[PDB]
Amino acid sequence: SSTMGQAGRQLAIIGDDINRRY
Amino acid sequence: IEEGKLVIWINGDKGYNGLAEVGKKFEKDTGIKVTVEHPDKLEEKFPQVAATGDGPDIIFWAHDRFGGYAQSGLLAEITPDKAFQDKLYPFTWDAVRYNGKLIAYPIAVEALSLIYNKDLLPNPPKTWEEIPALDKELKAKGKSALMFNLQEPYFTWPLIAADGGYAFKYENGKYDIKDVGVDNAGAKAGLTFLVDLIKNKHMNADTDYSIAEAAFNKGETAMTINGPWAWSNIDTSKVNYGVTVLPTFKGQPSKPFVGVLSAGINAASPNKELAKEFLENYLLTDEGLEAVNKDKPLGAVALKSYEEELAKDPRIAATMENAQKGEIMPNIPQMSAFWYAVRTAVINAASGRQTVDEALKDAQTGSELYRQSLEIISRYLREQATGAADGATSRKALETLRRVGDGVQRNHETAFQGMLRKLDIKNEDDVKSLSRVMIHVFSDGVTNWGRIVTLISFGAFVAKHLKTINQESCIEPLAESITDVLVRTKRDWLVKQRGWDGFVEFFHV
Ligand SMILES: OC[C@H]1O[C@H](O[C@H]2[C@H](O)[C@@H](O)[C@@H](O)O[C@@H]2CO)[C@H](O)[C@@H](O)[C@@H]1O
C-alpha cells in the first residue's frame, strides 16, 4: 500500500528519465 | 485440455446445477464425466485461455461475445445436421452465425423485464417519468421504488436505447463499425434521466446486481429490472411478484437488448464429438432444458418443442413482449470493446466523474483505443513472457516496444527487480491489486510517453515472473488492467498525442 505507492512513484521517475532521453 | 471428459463454463447466474444434472445423465449413459464451472468474468477469461489452447470444452454466454471468439479462431465450427437445425427456431440460428458459419448452439432467448412487488405496488408505473414521485411516496413508508444493477450497461441499455441510442448501425446486410450510436440526443436523454434519479437520491450510483437483488427479494424495493434467471430466487423469497413490460421513456418503449444464450465448442478441445453428443442429444431436449430451467429459468428456449410447452407462462410472455420492443445484439468482434466503453461511460456519468454528454461523447473513440491498445499490450507481454513471437500501426508499435520496452527493462532492471520483489506477487489477487500501482504512476498529474512505455515495460517484466511462478494465465488480465488505466484515465492525452502512431513517432530512431 505504501509499497504500491512507492513502486508507482518509482515507475514515474523512471518514466520521466525515459521521456527526457527520447 | 483433458481428453475423455467435458469441462463446461457457464455464468454463475444461470442454472449450472441443472446443467450438471444433465451432465450426470450423460455420464450414466457414456461413462464420461462432465464438470460444470462458473468462473468470474468468464466472458473475458475464455478468450484469454482458449487462445493458448486451454480452457473448457464448451463455453456458454450470450451470443454477442461469440463473433469475436470465432474471429480469433477459438471456436470449432459446429456440425448439426439439417434435421437437428429444424428443431430450433431459425432466428436463434441466425444469432450464432458468423461469416456464414454456425459457431455455437443456441439455447434460449433472453430479455430484461420489469419485476414488481404486487403487495407494495399492485399497479406499477407505465412510465419512467412517474418513478421519482413514486419513490418519494414509498420512502415515506420506509420503501423505495426501484433498484437494479447500475454497474453493467446491459441493465441501463433499455432506457438509453428508448429515445434513440443504438450500438452499431445495420444497413445493407451488415453493421457499420464506424457508426456507434450513444453520442446522440436520445441516448443522452435516457442516461440523463438515470443520472437525475441518482442526483435526486431515488437511486444509488453504487447499486450492483447483488444489492438490487437482495433489496427486491427482501421486500425493501417495489421494483427491479432483471432477466428470467432471477425468477428462481424470487420464488424462494416468497415475494408476491409480477413480470411486466418495462416502463416507457418519452412515451417510447424501453428497448432491451436481446441475447441468445449459446454454447460454443473450444477449437482446442480434443472432445468435440463428445461435446456435440452432449449438446445435441442431452441438453437440447425437453428433458435437458427442463433440468436447467427448473434450476434457473432460461427464458424462451430455442428448441421449438419445449418452447411451446412453456409458452403459456405469463412471465415468458412478458419477456418476449419486451424482447419484441428491443434489438438483437450484434455479434461482431467489436462488441467487447463497445461494452467496455459504454460501461465506463455509464459509471462515469452516474458517479459524476463526467457529465452525461462528455461520457457518451467519449465512448466511440474509447472503444477503438481500448481494442487497439489491448491487442498491442497483450501481445508484447505474452511474447516477452514466453520468449517466442506468435494492422500496420500495431505492428510498428510492437517493434517499438521490442526496442524501447526491452531497453527499459535492461537499463532499469535493478529497480524493476526490487519493485516486483517488494510487491511480492504470489497469486491472482496480488496481480489484480497491481492496478493500484498503475494509478500511482500518474498520481502527480503528469502524463508522458516515457511513463506510459515504462508502465508497459514493467508489465512485461512482471509477466516474465508470472510464468516462472506458474501463473502464466494472469498475463492477459495484467495486460487488460494496464490497458484500462490508460484508456479510462488518459484517453484525452492519447487522443491529443495521436495514439499509437504518436507513440511510434515519439520513440523513432
Ligand atoms: O453489461 C454488458 C454485458 O451485457 C450482456 O451480458 C448479460 C448477459 O447477456 C445476461 O445473460 C446476463 O448474464 O447478464 C449479463 C449482464 O451482466 C452481454 O452479453 C455481455 O457481453 C456484456 O458484457
Image: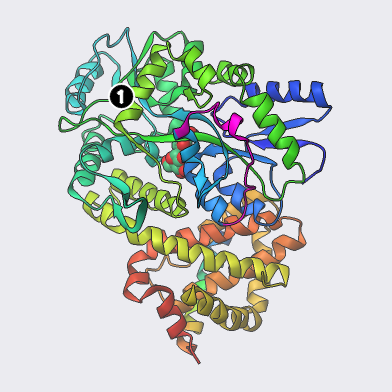
Q: Which residue is mark 1?
A: B146
B385 displayed left or right of B200 = right
Dominant secondary-structure state across the stretch colored magenta: loop
Q: Amino acid at mark 1?
A: Leu
Residue found at the very far bottom of the displayed protein: B509
Q: Residue at x 62, y 69 (%)?
A: B460
Residue B44: x %, y % from top left: 56, 48
Asked if the beta carbon under badge 1 is closer than 8 A to the nearest atom of ligand 1, the reply is no
Name the image quarter holding the N terminus of chain A.
bottom right
What residue is drawn where x is 63% and y is 75%?
Answer: B415
In this figure, what is the number of numbered marks?
1
**Vertical position of residue B233 compared to residue B422: above or below:** above
Q: Is residue B294 above or below residue B439?
A: above
Q: Is residue B340 visible?
A: yes
Foreground pick, B64 / B452: B64
In this picture, is B349 found above or below B386? above
Task: Between residue B71 and residue B437, name the one nearer to us.
Answer: B71
Where residue B339 appears, as percent x and y from the top left, is: 41, 48
What's drawn in magenta, residue-wise?
B72-90
